[PDB]
Image (spheres, coloured by chain):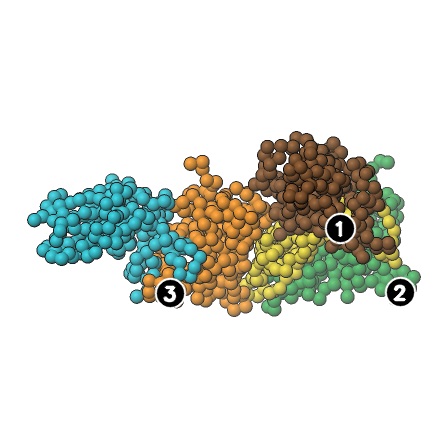
Chain colours: A cyan, B orange, C brown, D green, E yellow
Amino acid sequence: TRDETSIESFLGRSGCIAMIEFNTSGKGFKTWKVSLQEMAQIRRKYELFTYTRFDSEITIVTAAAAGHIVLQFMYVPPGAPVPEKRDDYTWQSGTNASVFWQEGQPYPRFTIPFMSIASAYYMFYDGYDGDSAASKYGSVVTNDMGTICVRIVTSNDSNIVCRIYHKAKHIKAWCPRPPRAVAYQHTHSTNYIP
Amino acid sequence: IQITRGDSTITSQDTANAVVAYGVWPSYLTPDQPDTSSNRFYTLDSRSWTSASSGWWWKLPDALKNMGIFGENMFYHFLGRSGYTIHVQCNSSKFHQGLLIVAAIPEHQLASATSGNVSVGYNHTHPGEQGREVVNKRPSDDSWLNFDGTLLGNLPIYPHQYINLRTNNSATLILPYVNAVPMDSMLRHNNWSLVIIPICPLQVQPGGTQSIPITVSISPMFSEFSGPRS
Amino acid sequence: IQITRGDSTITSQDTANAVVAYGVWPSYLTPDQPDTSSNRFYTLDSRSWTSASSGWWWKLPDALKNMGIFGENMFYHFLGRSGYTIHVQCNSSKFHQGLLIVAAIPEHQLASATSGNVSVGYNHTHPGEQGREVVNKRPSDDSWLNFDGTLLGNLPIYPHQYINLRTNNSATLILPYVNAVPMDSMLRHNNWSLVIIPICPLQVQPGGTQSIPITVSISPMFSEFSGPRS
Amino acid sequence: IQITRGDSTITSQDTANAVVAYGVWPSYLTPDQPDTSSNRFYTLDSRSWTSASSGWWWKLPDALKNMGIFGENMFYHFLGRSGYTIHVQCNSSKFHQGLLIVAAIPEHQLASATSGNVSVGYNHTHPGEQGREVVNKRPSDDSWLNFDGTLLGNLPIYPHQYINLRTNNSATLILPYVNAVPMDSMLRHNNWSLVIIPICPLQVQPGGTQSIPITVSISPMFSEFSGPRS
Amino acid sequence: MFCGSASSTLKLLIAYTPPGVGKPKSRREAMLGTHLVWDVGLQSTASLVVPWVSASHFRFTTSAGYITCWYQTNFVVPDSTPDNAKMVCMVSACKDFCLRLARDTNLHT
């Protein structure tokens, strides 16, 4: 009994953390910097803790509307260069992880390791990127988790939507915190005023 | 009784009743150290608690950056690490009444007093030994929202003690070093915030002393530094 | 070979050939201590020895009053005590020639350059790390009278070594603490004077380097202080 | 607790914390005695301590000359001898404050209040059980000069205790017989003076009791007499 | 020794400053030195032992440093209590104390 209140049960359930959409007719690619802060319901559960550490399993559910479409999904790890164009050199780099997926095949899945240079992710961070009045404060300073990039490989009028399902695995969590009592206004910020 | 650390001495009988944060005693970093010249009690200027007070906070190590050998070690090394003993004393008569929560919050990332995505500014998050007494880049005044959008009734999830003026005039928190890295910049980042909030406001009848002093004494514990420079 | 003390390192093969003043090794005071953070080598700015040079002197501890932890300990304590290692190096070609006496004088009470009962002034007897290069309260210029009315040929009665440029480029003096009291004011009183005097003046032919550097490195040894203040 | 001597009883918990003058317990004279009928506690009329009080003194055995069997023995024998227990009690609230020194002075030879070689008169030096409350043959009023030309801050060289009203309401002095002869005239000569002086004057707010009682209880100890007459 | 009422409470900072350092100008400067934070409510008496600190084994009878006292808190009392009190300071030798080379002089006439 009480395994359903284990941290693996509470934080380790798959959820749609991002919603990549793009069109084709540059243009035919999209990118998303990976964070758990986008969706309030996911964010609130992770923010019950000060630090968390997990590997993460990505599953990408794709729907498309105008032969079968071919997509490249690319994971760019922290501090590596992110694509600027649909056929940039970054898509060919053997240091990025790519999965090529073709329509009607089972949805693509991969696990990213815990990538951070610190031993856990900071859900909160009481410090700065530097000394300046312009310097960032809070959990945006730490926690580059990488970027998910999508392009169509096929030659040509179509709309593509990719739901990024994420499951945290082998989860550890430290220093419990009061639950968020008021609405989230912005990503990584503790600000609450409407 | 008497507590002595370095050339500093403080008096309190309650010292054995300390809360050890997360049940972990402070310690030196394991293989996977200036001692008592650094590890003194530094006693801050006493706060005036009144019926109007909203509470106070300090950031650590920031509150000690001007404090003797430990404050110099924060500038003369690239990275540092310490635990703390925080001793809070609140001397009063039998005719005063009031309740403080004394809490230590790890990574107390403050919300702003404003509606935008605007961050709290460095001048506001680093108030030094004076702390902030609670009343566009300034932090929240909402002590009832823990200055971070969370309810004050839930603040006891953090390492804490109550000072109830009828029962006890003091609280002691023992804080281990808490971070996701072994050592860190002591000047860019605060591991802990000390928060003192009156749950039940001070009451006393006229002719009693209308302000009671809250005295905060902080000792570094197991302090470690690396990258020394002259 | 290499000699290392604290975070300071100097290179010289001659180090085993040191003169221990009066045959007494420096030591901590007996029952009838900051170690290597204080006890570094401090290397002074090199003197230019030329055919015109009359000699140089420094007073100890005065020459170290601005030097790191040891210099701070001289202001932050009422009384102090130390020995010294003095290492003097004098790099030259096989075609240069000259003879220095390097001597340490205990209680080198200077004579004035004047005929009255007038004392030498504090500004003149405390020249700091620069020392005095020899040319109404100023000291004597007579290096041939040891600046004190005694002959230079008799200077070898003090702890000394020769630097003869054909034979050896260096001298080392190990000085115990010498005083009639266990500890003393480091700022009002100098236990030792380092004196460097050319007996045979520098000669070299034109197209050789006309100035040769004399480099003085001083390490405190067994330094002790009492009456600490912030 | 309760202390009983003869048919007299007094109440105080502090009795084990007595000062024994010069570390010598009172005793009967050695080969080189009426007991408990003489050796009662005699309780004097209580003094009114106020913010205006300069202090009080009594002479021993003189203060007991009218006191029962001991007082009769001083007239009905030529020579006598005794020690004393002096118990001083000073009942007060938690809201009163003040400091007494209670001291016993051997041979307290009083100065006069006058400039000549004139002695203090017998009527003034023998005030009996009433003592003197401090305001041409009358004694000094200068309690700050111990009535004898010596400073009050140095009065602790004598057998003494403090009564600090926050800490203790009582003092006990055990006095041996002190004289340069084995036995002496009890009526011509006083071995001891009890002196009670407020160092910190009494303070209390209006509506508190403005006078606090100082109650002095004296018991003879090991009393001895010789040359009996009817 | 603190001589306020049993209802009176206060913290004092008692600081020792070594010879040659110079007397503290503030409670913060005194706190950075050798000191006791004394709660007079809890303890009616405090003590400080100043050990011997000079270059010679003796010094003449005509610095040794300063003792200074500072408010750490305001003076706290309930109603019907004096809003002031007195403190008494005392000195004595320890068992190591020694005097040498007797002299007679007009310091008393």
How far apart, in angstroms, are the residues tagged by discs 3 and 1? Answer: 70 Å
Tag 1: residue type? Answer: Val
Q: Position of residue B196 (x, y in %)?
A: 45, 57
Label 3 to label 2: alpha-carbon separation: 79 Å
Give the residue type at disc 3: Ala
Query: In this view of the protein, can residue C159 be seen by the observer?
Result: yes
Taking depth in this image into account, of E91 and A28 the one nearest to the observer is A28
**Is residue C14 rendered to the left or right of residue A136?**
right
Can you identify the residue that label 3 sits on? Answer: B113
Residue that carries the numbered disc 1 in the rendered image: C135
**In the image shown, does D193 or C130 lie closer to the viewer?**
C130
Q: Who is closer to the viewer here, B193 or C195?
A: C195
Whether labels 3 and 2 belong to a single chain: the reply is no
Q: Residue at x 44, y 66 (%)?
A: B135
Q: Could you tell me if the residues under marks 3 and 1 are in contact, i.e. CB atoms within 8 Å?
A: no
Of discs 2 and 1, which sits in the foreground?
1
Q: Amino acid at mark 2?
A: Ser
Which chain letter goes with mark 2? D
Q: Is residue C79 left or right of residue B225?
A: right
| Residue C156 image position (x, y, % from top left) | 78, 36
Q: Residue at x 49, y 55 (%)?
A: B63
| Image mark for residue D115 | 2
